[PDB]
Amino acid sequence: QIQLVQSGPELKKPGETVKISCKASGYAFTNYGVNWVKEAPGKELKWMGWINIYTGEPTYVDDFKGRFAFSLETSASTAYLEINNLKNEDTATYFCTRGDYVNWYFDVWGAGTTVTVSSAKTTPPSVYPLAPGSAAQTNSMVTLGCLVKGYFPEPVTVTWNSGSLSSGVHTFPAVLQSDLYTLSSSVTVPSSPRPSETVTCNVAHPASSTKVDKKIVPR
Amino acid sequence: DVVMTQIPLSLPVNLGDQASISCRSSQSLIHSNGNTYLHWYLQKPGQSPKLLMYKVSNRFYGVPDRFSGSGSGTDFTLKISRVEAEDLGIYFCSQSSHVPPTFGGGTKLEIKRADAAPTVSIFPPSSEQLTSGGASVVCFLNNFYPKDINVKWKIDGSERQNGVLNSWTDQDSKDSTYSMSSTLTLTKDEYERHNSYTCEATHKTSTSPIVKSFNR
Ligand SMILES: CC(=O)[C@H]1CC[C@H]2[C@@H]3CCC4=CC(=O)CC[C@]4(C)[C@H]3[C@H](OC(=O)CCC(=O)O)C[C@]12C
């Protein structure tokens, strides 16, 4: 099983540094390079630097100098990335890749270590009900929703009727508005269910140990 | 830095058709030693990329018979031959000939199906939010294809800019559709000194806008 194994996801606030690890097992560590690749939200795969295990020497692509330090401790088959004075800009998933000396490709990638840098402190989510505002169904069906607003960090689990409403629900992706996330989900039911049967949306937010059920009720 | 660009951004494909991504370089990829280092990666979602093709035309180990590289100089294309369901992902091409190796933007493979129009809904501020000082109006644009749709938020007869936020779902796997939700946001006060709010969706399936409103 020849992999490059990377440490976990990290949540960190400006300034604070973070030592990312990348451990090799399976192959001859010394005669391949460990290249570091950055994947930032809706930016490109920026190639960061490289550390060749013969020489011990780092080449950084000085679009990253002085904060980001590649280090290594070879006897332990582990290559490391340290970022120092973390700014907000670094929120990304840093992969380490095994690169080769003959064909120059990257052929074993590590799984990713997402760093999230922020300054919000954990906030539980305000959950609010969305009900039709008396707008009357075009074709035989209704769409209710939940709006989970102003929370940190992620994830949030929105489920409808405790898992029982699956087809029809559309939980969208979280978006920021000042440090805190907002996200909404929608369920589309037969109008022979709402308001005859109940429709409850359950938002759970494990990071603060809050779970908030909200039943949607007319409007 | 060499600037490698890919196009299309997405490729509608019916599983079975052939497909071609086409990368391109702002400098040439033939290296003094004679080799060209254009490599191609496939990143299936929530993952780390898997090497597919190296040195323009060479397939990596195991990577399926249905692929082919081509090109020279600055133009290269990867051809998938009869798309199966597991080839679906973002493809990136990379130059590894000039330091720094650089990366392309990607081309997402996506399934194509018949045009669908969005069943759009608008929702007025819940009372428990006004109770605290805000009012987010929320419009959901659901179950539409294809992925471009433009959402106007006409907030008083006029059009509003700020406080809208959008978020899309990915290609909904069950029906190969998309979904969008925009939340216009006003201060409680700033909501209640006003009459109608309309979310307005402009999109291929429509002759003229498919718009929804409430007022107070
Ligand atoms: C094994 C590895 O990490 C690979 C992955 C991508 C490769 C580099 C891609 C960039 C590159 C372009 C060149 O033509 C010069 C060599 C280099 C700089 C390649 C290195 O070769 C070299 O000769 C540098 C190695 C050395 O001689 O110190 C080895 C790399 C960094």
Image: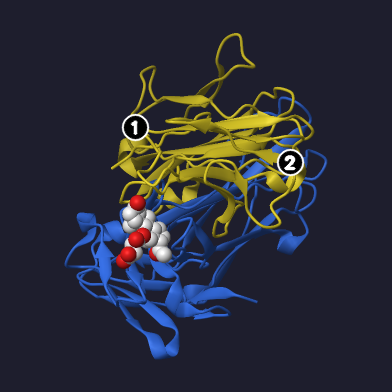
Chain colours: A blue, B yellow
**Residue placed at 65% from the left, 28% from the top?**
B145
Query: Which of the two labelled residues, at mark 1 and mark 2, occupies the earlier sequence position?
Result: 1
Looking at the picture, do discs 1 and 2 lie on one chain? Answer: yes
Residue A194 left/right relative to A122: right
The outermost residue toward the left is A66
Chain label for disc 1: B
Q: Find numbered disc 2 in the image and state the secondary structure of the residue it sits on.
A: loop
Q: Which amino acid does label 1 sit on?
A: Ser
Whether residue B29 is visible here, answered yes or no, is yes
Mark 1 in CB contact with mark 2 (< 8 angstroms)? no
For mark 2, what is the residue? B66
The reply to whether residue B196 is visible in this rendering is no
At which x and y percent is residue B195?
41, 25
View extreme (top): residue: B207
Front-most of residues B206 and B57: B57
Which residue in the structure is indicated by mark 1?
B26
Residue A7 percent coordinates (x, y): 46, 78
Q: Mark 2 lies on which chain?
A: B
Q: What residue type is labelled 2?
A: Arg
Q: Where is residue A95 in the image (x, y as percent from the top left)?
A: 44, 64
- Residue occupying image coordinates x 41% and y 40%: B165
Neighbourhood count class around disc 2 (C-alpha, 10 Å): few under 14, some 14–19, many 20 upward: few
Count of residue discs: 2
Q: For residue B32, what is the image quadrant?
A: top left
Question: Which of the 4 image quarters holds residue B159?
Answer: top left
Neighbourhood count class around disc 1 (C-alpha, 10 Å): few under 14, some 14–19, many 20 upward: few
Residue furthest out toward the right: A192
In the rendered view, would you say A206 is above or below A114? below
Q: Which of A217 and B143 is in front in this view?
A: B143
Q: Is residue A142 left or right of residue B132?
A: right
